[PDB]
Length: 316
Ligand SMILES: CCC[C@H](NC(=O)[C@H](CC(C)C)NP(=O)(O)CNC(=O)OCc1ccccc1)C(=O)O
Ligand SMILES: [Ca+2]
Ligand SMILES: [Ca+2]
Ligand SMILES: [Ca+2]
Ligand SMILES: [Ca+2]
Ligand SMILES: [Zn+2]
Image (cartoon, rainbow, N blue to C red; front, side):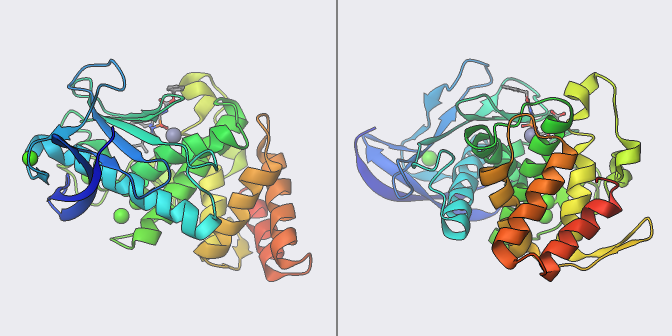
């Protein structure tokens, strides 16, 4: 909408107060003009028609319970935009400052979030398995990263390419969580998953097996559920990424960690310069090795560590 840029204040899903960029024209809208061609957050009003209505508020204060998922969707989209711009010199998901759109309050008791090809969508959860999913910065960045992937590598959402697609979203979701530096970890969705159970998560990158996912290629799922296991086999790549950054010895194979920033540079380069829609795990290894070679040199520790990590998870 046409209007003047303003700054509202509210509380997110976890009860934390934050400022949000809004736009004033009769109402205050969740429209952030400070980033690219805008970040726009919508109310789906418990229905499934998208995007719904651009979020409008009478007083620029967002402290109602109903407001919380919108506050976090809007704010964490901003953080994710900043990560891609400041860290990777990428302007929005398309590299050309495309407007970023999110809808919250999607459906009823909806235990998921997704990128629908054009925008991000967040359920409120059923209050048992999830609370509103935009409350997780790793979740928001996971979803926006699907858009990045679709505009770049274009990894097809099934089988091995699909598991890479998923791992890329978990990896950058986590790197954005570290970027914001609030309770960061290598777990996925812990801030919004199972409010009745402390200390768990939807997935773990550091130990995928904790939540039932493979941490070695020999344990890959080859059935048809979950698009050929895209959220399951992602554990193999998530484990490799974790090892590249933090190091460790996994099934007897030792990996020297090189840190999160270098992990991010290597995987961002792989995603944007080497991966294709049909890339498999073996091809990801090659892409990551080449990316590390480009950035740090063939004889670098960084290249050696990438190889160690993929060796450790059984990907040659
Ligand atoms: C409990 C849900 C677990 C998993 N979802 C996830 O891991 C994350 C949300 C997490 C980070 C909180 N959602 P996601 O991976 O974006 C869901 N993906 C998805 O719906 O893809 C199908 C699709 C939807 C729309 C267009 C094209 C394809 C899943 O969908 O199995
Ligand atoms: Ca208000
Ligand atoms: Ca965390
Ligand atoms: Ca996390
Ligand atoms: Ca929990
Ligand atoms: Zn995903």
